[PDB]
Image: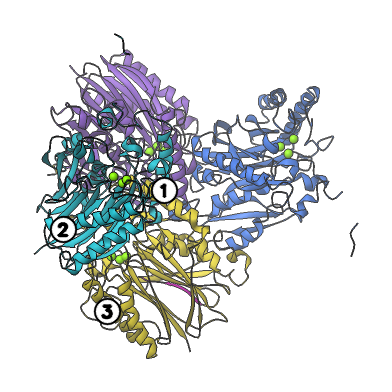
Chain colours: A purple, B blue, C yellow, D cyan
Amino acid sequence: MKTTISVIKADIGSLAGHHIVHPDTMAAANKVLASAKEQGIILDYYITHVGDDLQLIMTHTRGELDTKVHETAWNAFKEAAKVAKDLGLYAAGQDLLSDSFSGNVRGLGPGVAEMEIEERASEPIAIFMADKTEPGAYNLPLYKMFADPFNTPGLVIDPTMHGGFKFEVLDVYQGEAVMLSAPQEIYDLLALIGTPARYVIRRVYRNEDNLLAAVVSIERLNLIAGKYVGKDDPVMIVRLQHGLPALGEALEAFAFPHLVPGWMRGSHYGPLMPVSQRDAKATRFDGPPRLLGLGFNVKNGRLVGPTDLFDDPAFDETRRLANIVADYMRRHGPFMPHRLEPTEMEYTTLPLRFKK
Amino acid sequence: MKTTISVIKADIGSLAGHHIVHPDTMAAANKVLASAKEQGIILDYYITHVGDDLQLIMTHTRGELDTKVHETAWNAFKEAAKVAKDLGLYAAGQDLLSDSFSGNVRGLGPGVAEMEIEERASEPIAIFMADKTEPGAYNLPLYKMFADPFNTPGLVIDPTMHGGFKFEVLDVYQGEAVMLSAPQEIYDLLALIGTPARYVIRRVYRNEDNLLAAVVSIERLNLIAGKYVGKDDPVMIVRLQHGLPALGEALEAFAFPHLVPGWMRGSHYGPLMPVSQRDAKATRFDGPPRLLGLGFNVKNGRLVGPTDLFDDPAFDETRRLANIVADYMRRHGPFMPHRLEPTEMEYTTLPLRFKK
Amino acid sequence: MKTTISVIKADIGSLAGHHIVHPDTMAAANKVLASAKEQGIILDYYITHVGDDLQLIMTHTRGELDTKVHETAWNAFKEAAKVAKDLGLYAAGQDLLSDSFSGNVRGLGPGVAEMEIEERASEPIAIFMADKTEPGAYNLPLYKMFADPFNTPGLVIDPTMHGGFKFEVLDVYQGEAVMLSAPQEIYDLLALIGTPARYVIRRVYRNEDNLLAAVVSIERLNLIAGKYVGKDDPVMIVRLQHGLPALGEALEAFAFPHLVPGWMRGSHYGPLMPVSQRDAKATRFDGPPRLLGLGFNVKNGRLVGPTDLFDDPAFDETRRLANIVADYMRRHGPFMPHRLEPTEMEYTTLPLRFKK
Amino acid sequence: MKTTISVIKADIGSLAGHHIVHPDTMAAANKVLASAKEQGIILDYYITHVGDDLQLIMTHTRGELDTKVHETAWNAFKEAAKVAKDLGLYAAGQDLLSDSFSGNVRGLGPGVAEMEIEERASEPIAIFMADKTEPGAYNLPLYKMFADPFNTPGLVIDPTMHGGFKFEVLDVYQGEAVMLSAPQEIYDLLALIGTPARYVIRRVYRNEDNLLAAVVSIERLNLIAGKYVGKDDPVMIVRLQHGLPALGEALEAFAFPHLVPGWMRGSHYGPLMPVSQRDAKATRFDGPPRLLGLGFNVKNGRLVGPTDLFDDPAFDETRRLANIVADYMRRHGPFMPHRLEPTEMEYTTLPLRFKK
Ligand SMILES: [Mg+2]
Ligand SMILES: [Mg+2]
Ligand SMILES: [Mg+2]
Ligand SMILES: [Mg+2]
Ligand SMILES: [Mg+2]
Ligand SMILES: [Mg+2]
Ligand SMILES: [Mg+2]
Ligand SMILES: [Mg+2]
Ligand SMILES: [Mg+2]
Ligand SMILES: [Mg+2]
Ligand SMILES: [Mg+2]
Ligand SMILES: [Mg+2]
C-alpha cells in the first residue's frame, strides 16, 4: 500500500501580463479538487500558485500517471481557465494546449512531478515550484543536494548516506535517459547536466537501497509545441531526512541564486530568486525567476503543512544578491550571455544582404 | 463599440502638509462615483491616492474628453474638497482652480490621461500615478519602454514589434505637437524630450497599425496658473502585451530611479521612487517623488485588479538607491542642479546693488 | 598619401601558465622592429603585452594587408618565440600555427587590426587589446560607442554626428558580411551582434562621408584550427574626436564590465576587466578577461604616447564590480551560463548508456 | 635525468616581533647559496620571505632528502641566524631546534617541500608559502584544485584529467599515510582532511599515470618539540598545465580566504590572506595568516621568474573579505571557535577548586 504525491501545474491565465494567478481561478480549481476529495479519488490536496502558474498538490493512492488523477487536474485547470476567460485575464488557458484530455496531462501542456512511495517512519518532504524558468533550473540544486559534500555534509558524516546517490538524467532532445552514480561518476554527470536545456535530472535515488528521493517535472513546452509558447515553469518533490538530505541541506542548495534560463520572453538568463508565497509573482522584466518552497509531512495520505520555506530572514541576502545580479545582467540588453544561446532562441521568433 | 479608460486626478487637500490624502475625502469621492456607476454613466471605477493626489480610475463608453465623465470627476473632487475643508486639511481644494466646471477638467486644475480603445483579445494595462513631479518625468521611462532595445528586447526579437513605435511630443510652452518615429528618428526625439519641462511625450503609437499604446496627462499647473501652485503630479496609462511592451518591459523602465523635477516647493530634482500603495506618501523633503503602479485587465468595461506593481522585492534596491541619491542630492542645499534651473524657478517666488 | 596603423599580435608563450609575456621575449621582438624602423619599412612602433599576448603597434605607409609589414611582425614573433622556447616558457610559439609565413599573418595564428587613413587635422586614437576573450567581446562596446545615444551624446547634440554610423558585421561562420546603418537598422543590428560568437562587428564607418572610424581583429583560432587552441584575444583601433566619438565616449563604452566568452580553458563567461598596463596579466581562473587601452596621437606616421587609459580612479568601481561578478559567476561551477553554450564548447574536448 | 625542486624554509628571527625577515639575514643566506651554486651543488635558487619565514627555493639534480642540499640550507639558515643575533632580532634562530645538522633538515626545525621530477615539454609551477599557520591549511585548497569540479573544470572538460587525482594523506599523529582516489573516495577523503591538524595532504598524483603533481611540507613543530614553539608555516609546490590544474585553477583554490589555525600565539583561527611580496608580513594580531604565491617555469634546472601571483587586482576582494572576517573573528576574544580546540591548545601553556 503506497501513497502517491502528485504535483500537477499549469498556467491558465494571469492578471496584467504573466504576473500572478487571480484568486477567482484558484477558487474554481478548488471546487473540482474538493469534489474529487469528497469522492475519495484523492485523499488530500493543497492549491497555490507561483507567479502565473496554478499549482495542484495532491495525495492519493492511485499511482503515478493515473488517468483519473490527471483528468481531475485537467478539469480543475479547465474550470480555472473558464473563470480566467470570463475575467478577461491575459493568456487565458495558456498551458492548455489540447482541446481535450486523454490518458494523462503529459504532452497536453501541464507539468507534472509525482512519486509513488511507501511512507517512511515519518515522511517530511519539500515541494519546489518555479516561475519563469525551465526544468533544468533544478540541475545545479539537485547536484548540490545529493552529490556535493560542501552542500550536504551527511554524505561525509552520516553512515547511511556515504554510499551516495544516483541520477536519472533525461536527454530531452533525444528522449533517452541514463543513470549516473555519485561520487564515482560526478565528472560525467556534470559534463551533461551543465547543459540544462538538454540534459535534465528527472529523478534521484539512493544507491544503497534504490530509494526514490526526488522527482522533477520534465515537460518542456518548446519541445511539445515546436515553438516558444511560454516558460515550462517546473516543479520538484524532494523527500527529506532519514538518510536523505535534511530540510536544511535541501534549502542550502538554493541559498545561491544561480542564473537560469527563461525570464522575459523566454529569452534570457536571470537569477533564481527564492521567495515567500506573498512574493511569488513576476514583476521587473517579467521576473526575476521566482522559487516557492513548501514543506509538508505526509501522514496516511494527509498533507500536514505547508510551511513557507523561503519566507525567512536566512534568505534575505539571497534575495538581495538576486536583485543586484538582475540589474547587472540587464545592463547587457539583448546580448549573450544575458540573452539565450542561439540553439534555444531558435524556438522564439528571432529566426524570422550578406555578401561574400 | 469602444471602451474608454479615464484616469482623472486632483489634489483636494491633505493631512499635515502635502503628505497624504485623508480617507474621509476618498469616501466622499466614492459616493459620487458609486452613483455615476449606478446610473450607467461609467461602467466601473477604482479610487486611490498617490501622496496628496486623489485618483479616479474610470471605465466607460463615452469617449475621450466627455463632458459628463469629466463633470462626474469634478463633482467627486468637489465633495472630497468639502470634506477636506470640514476637516481643516492643508490646502483644501488645492487643484480646483476654477470655481465652476465647464466642458471638461482640462485647464481647471485636475490632470487627465484617457484613451478610447477597442479591447484586444485580452486587455492588460498598467496605470502609473506620481506625486511631487511633472508629466515630463515619464519621458525617459516611455523612451525606454517603446524605443530602447536594452529595455524592451521585444523590439529585437518579436516580429510584431520590429517596426517600432512613434511618439507624439508636445511642446507645452508653444502648444504644438510633432510625431517622431523610432528607431529612425531617435536622435531627434532625444534632442527634444531630454528637456522634459518643455517637450513631453503625450501619446505613443505602434508604427505598423497606428495602435494607441500609451497616454500621459499633460496638464501643467505652472502654465495653467502663470505661477507655481503645486506640482502637476502626472498619470499615464500603458497598454501591454500582444506586440506592445510586456508588463515586465514597462516595469523595467522604472527600475532606474531617475532624477525628476518637483519635490520640495516644486523647486528641486530628486529620484523617482517606485512604491507600494502603503508607501505612496510624501515625507523627507516632501518626497522623494513617489510612483504608484497598478496593473489591471479591462474586460467589457470592467476593471479586473488592481495588482500593486512596485510592492515587490524586485524593486527593493531601486528604493534603496533612491534613498541614497536623495541624501546625496540634499547635500547640495539650494544649489543647481539639485535646485531647478532658472527658467523653471521663474514660476516660483524666487524672482521676487549691482555695480558695473 | 596615407598613414596605416597596424596592430598585429600573437601569443608566443608565457610565464607560469597563460599568465604574462616575459620581458626577454618583448626585447627580441623589439630588435626586429627596431631594424624595420631603421630600414624605413615602418615609421614608428610601440611594443607591449596584455596577459600572454605580445602586441606590435606599428605605423607605416604600406597599406592594409602589406606582405612586408606582416612578415616583419611574423619575424618578430618568431624571434620572441625562440627566446620563449630557450626560457622553457609555457606554450612557446602558441599562436604561430604555421611553420612558415606567406602573404600575410591572417590564417597563420596572429591577430591583426589595421586601418589605412588620411590623418585628420589631428589624429587621436585609442587602441584596445584584450586577453582571455574573442573578437565579439567588442560588439557591445562598439554598439554603445557608435549607436547608443545614452553612451555617446554627440549623436544627439553634435550636428556632425547626427547622421549616425554604419557597421560592417561579419558572419564568421559563413564568411560573409553585411552593412547595417544606425539608427534606422539598430533592431536588425542587435538581432545579429547579440550573438558575438557568430556575428562580429569588423569595421565602423560614419554615414555622412563613409569615414572609416574603427577596425576589429576578426581572426578566430577555433575557426582557423578546427578546434580550441586558445582564446583569440582581440584588438581594436578607434579613431576619436572631430565628429567621431570623444575619447570619453569610447571609454564610457567600457565602464560596464560585461560578460564575455573565454576565460578558463576558453570555456566560460566572465566580466571584461579594464586594467592598467601593470595589471594586464591573467590570474584567478586564468583571468578575469583583461582589457588594456592605450591612447595615442598619430602625427606624420609618428606615434605620440601612449597614455594608459584605464589606469585611473574613474575605473576603480568598474574593476570592483568585475571582481564581484567574477566570484558570482564562479559559484556556478561547470554549469551554463558560466560555462559556454554547446555550439561553442564543441571546439573543446568536451565532446570526447542512454536508454529509450 | 631528473630535476629536483626543493623549497626549504625556516624562521631564523625577525624584526619587532614575529613580523618580518630582516634583509641583512637574507643577504647572509644568499652568500651561502651563491657559493653552492658556484660549486655546482645546486643549479639555481631564489631567496625570499613570507612574514618571519626565510624561504630557500632551489633547483638541483641531487634528488629528494639530499644530505648536501639540506646541509647547504642548514648552513644558510645558520649564517642568517648569526646575523639575526648580531642585530638583536626577536627569536634569533627560532626554528633551528638542533645545535647541529645530520642527515637532512626534517626534525631539526626547518620545513621542506621537494619533488624530483622529469621536466615536461614545459614545466610551469606555483610555489605557495604561508606564515602564521600549519600544513593542514593547504588541505581545502588542494582538495579544490585536484578534486572539485566547481574549482577545476578541467576535471569535467579535459579528457586528460577525467581520470582524476589521488591524495597521499598523512596521519601526522600516528605517522602513517593512506592513498585515496578522487572522485570515487571523496567522501572518505573529506572525513579525514576536514580535520587538518591531524590529517594532512602530503602529495597529490594523477591517477592515469601516477604523475607527481603537488607536495606539501609536513613538518609540525608542535609534534617535533612536544610543545608550542611557533607556527609550522608551510610551503607547497604545485605543477601546472598539461593535464594538471591550470595556473588559474590553482589560484581559484585560494580565492576564498578560509579559516586556518595559527595566528596569534599559535592559538587561533583566522582567514588565510593571499598577498603580494611587499604585503607578506604579519601585523594585526600577528597576522592575519599570509600566503605568498610565486609562479616559475623550470628549464634545465633554471628558475625562470618569479611572477608574484596574488599581487593583482583579482584578489583585492579576497583580501577585503579576509579583513572583514578577521575583525568578526576577533570579537570572539578567547572563545572557541576563534581560539583553538582543546586538543591543539594542549601544546600551549593553557594547560598550566572544583567540587562534586
Ligand atoms: Mg503566463
Ligand atoms: Mg509561469
Ligand atoms: Mg509557463
Ligand atoms: Mg498638495
Ligand atoms: Mg501631489
Ligand atoms: Mg500637485
Ligand atoms: Mg597563452
Ligand atoms: Mg591570451
Ligand atoms: Mg590567445
Ligand atoms: Mg617567528
Ligand atoms: Mg612564521
Ligand atoms: Mg613559524
Structural crowding at the residue carrying mark 1, measured as other residues with C-alpha within 10 Å and reported as few (<14), some (14–19) or many (≥20)? some
**Residue type at numbered disc 1:** Glu
Residue found 58% across the figure and 73% down from its top: C243
Span colored in magenta: C210-217
Badge 3 local density, few (<14 within 10 Å), some, or many (20+)?
many
Vertical relation: A157 (above or below) C303: above
Query: Residue D172, how many percent across, how many down?
Result: 16, 38
Three-letter code, disc 3: Glu
Q: Residue at x 27, y 62 (%)?
A: D30
Marks 3 and 1 on same chain: no
The residue located at (72%, 54%) in the rendering is B198
- For disc 1, the marked residue is D317
> Could you tell whether C164 is left or right of B356 in the image?
left
The residue at the point 20 percent across, 50 percent down is D112
Q: CA distance from mark 2 to mark 3?
A: 37 Å
Tell me the residue that label 2 is attached to: D69
Do the residues indicated by labels 1 and 2 lie within the same chain of the protein?
yes
How many numbered tags mark residues here? Answer: 3
Mark 1 belongs to which subunit?
A: D
Frontmost of labels 2 and 3 is 2
* Parent chain of label 2: D
Residue at image mark 3: C79
Q: CA distance from mark 3 to mark 1?
A: 39 Å
Residue A311 against residue D129 in the figure, above or below: above
